[PDB]
Image 1 (tube, rainbow over the protein chains, first blue to last red):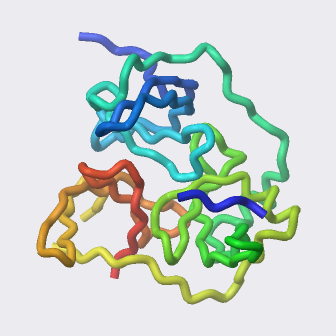
Image 2: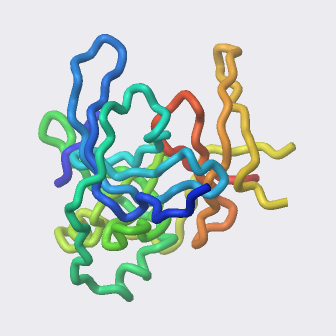
Length: 6
Length: 208
């Protein structure tokens, strides 16, 4: 569910 | 000339000015002062999952460093459970574009210093140090452990405790960069953290 950031 | 409390365990804030970009405002908590390179601090910043290494007092990008009076929490959690996750290969689910839950193979390395309800974790396809409150992923069903795994770290060649010893990373373009071993993973003794001079991230390597 966590967002993957750049 | 002076012996004082260091800033490990403290909340900090500071400006960050790099390149031609406008100035941002960073806030975080200092996890470690690296014994083999005491100018180097390991920090977990807010809103950034990747752990940073910064020479806070020397780095020109770091403007107006300030120690915050805010205290760091000691949240209630299942300790034995937390301990049982350490050293485990996992399948960690993240949100992918455009609507696709993605599985990232990873390895839980340790409970973090200072913020010990958070976990050191790295990923096979992205072998730098990350930090999450993994038990909330495990409770939400976004963390599957793999009891019998075949996990690949990038390899570090030798040529005798390695922490404190210097490395060179010879890139595919023929250029090199310097770094040093800053940590040996307690739960996984053949695995080390490396900090390169030219790079903010903490890199996770295994020995042959």
